[PDB]
View (cartoon, rainbow over the protein chains, first blue to last red):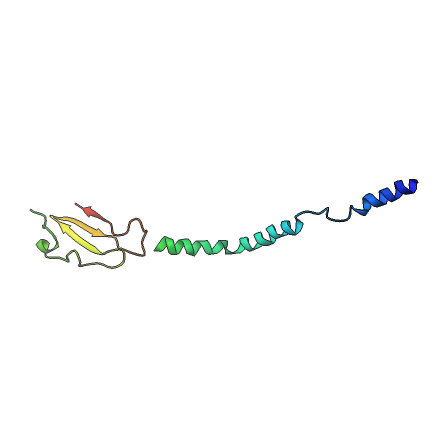
Length: 54
Length: 54
């Protein structure tokens, strides 16, 4: 019944390859989001300039 | 021996005379001359501002 001990090791592996990964689709998003942040930044200038001029 | 009370005393271009960008008046005061900032496309702050010349 080391087999159990085995099947234990199996069992603990059994419920070890499921739901043990939080928030990574969450995390990639941030950067994937933040990528979008990277772009309109330059627009701020003429926006300011417009506000600056006007 | 006396300054001109104004443009007209001098006989010259009055307040609403000589002007353009950032100049919505140009005025003499007993020889003390002054012009005003425009009221737009300016620093929102300095909008419509003057300083004399004596």
